[PDB]
Every structure is written in structure tokens, then in C-alpha cells.
Length: 216
Image (tube, rainbow, N blue to C red):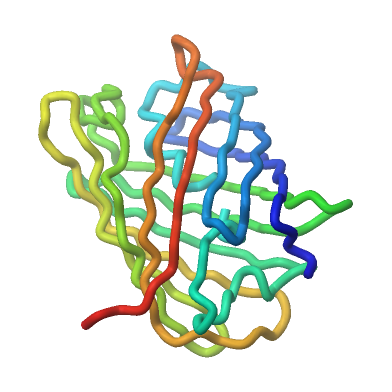
């Protein structure tokens, strides 16, 4: 009831990558039951970023995933209070990122607060040299544990040279009130940068995601 067929969000991120501090502010919109959303982000401090935007893009919205009727939606049920999440991203070349997020609702608008710390990225690696070209489509394997939902993703960034750059994502999602827990299930997702200015200080992105049962 609280999550309408069309919803907007506002987001603020404070982060650091290999010690370079930055801030991002943005706004987004989408269709939570259709699984689609777009966001427009601006770098407000530390721009232009000396690293790939692709590290940031998965940190900007779990209310917007399409679910079949028989899978309870952990995220939508958590409103109006909302949910938190905490993530580690471990990259194949030793780069590591921790992210924490709070999702709440104010005056009918979703409010996202993100903190990000990335370290140990090789100075000549694809992240610090901006050689990545977006994420491959992915499948997050979600499972319940003790009132929280945990997710694992094998993620891959495309490289400008045609190669790939792999990461493991581990996330815990925590509703702020009791909800009906789903069984373990999968979320298929595609995230794309759809526009940007020359130095990626203004960036638009789009995500489509849909939950489904595992086939085994």
C-alpha cells in the first residue's frame, strides 16, 4: 500500500576510494512492481572521480524489484519504516569495498543514505585507470537467515580491451520491522549507465530486476 506503482527516491553517498574522498547526491524514479528504475547522480565533492563509476553504480534500490505473486517481497513489506543493507565487494585483483545503506521513507519519497569505503585497488588496475565498461547481467542468490535476507552475487565488469574483471558481492539486507520471509530465490538484474557528462560528474543509470524461483 505504501509502495505505489510509481515512486521516487533521493540519495546521498559519502565515500572514499584508495583514500580519495567524494560525495554524490541524486534522485531517481521508477515502477516498483514492474522492476524498473532510473537515477540521475551528481558528484558534489571529490569530482571528477579518479576511479570507475561502475564501482558506485550498484550502491544507488531494493524496493524496485518485480516479484512473482508467490514470493513475499521482503523489501516492499518493510515500509514505511524501511530497511538497511551492508555489503562487501571483493574484486579479483585485491580491491575491496565495504558499503552500508539506510532506506527510509519521508513525505512519500524514498530516502537512501550510503557510506562507501574502497581500499587496496591496484594503482594501474581497471578501476583506478577507468578501464571498465559496465556490469554484465547478474543473478543475486538471496536466502533468509534469522529475519534477515542475505545475498551472494558473482559479478563481472566488462573491460575496454574485451576482457572481464570479476567480483564477489556479499550483502545482508535487514528490515526495520517484522515481515513475511521469502524462501531462498534469485534476482536477475541488468544495470546500465545510460548517459553521462564528459567527466562522469553527472551520470544517469537504469536498472531492471526481477525475482524468480531457482530451477536447481
